[PDB]
Length: 58
Image 1 (cartoon, helix red, strand yellow):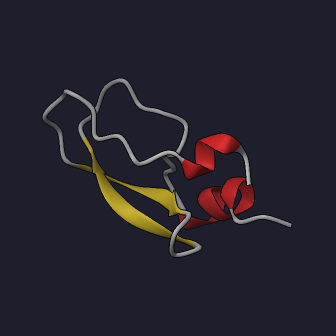
Image 2 (cartoon, rainbow, N blue to C red; image 1 turned 60 degrees about the vertical axis):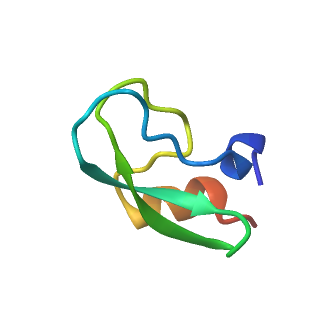
């Protein structure tokens, strides 16, 4: 996996509730989290397919 797929999902300091996918590397699955709307990190996907292609492995 890229390193960044192992990082926790980052809500950040803004107060939107935007539902995004992250790769949960402990589960081996892309899952939802709540993104606050600014200062996104890389383990933050608008779709499950995006997340799987980047983080789900060979």
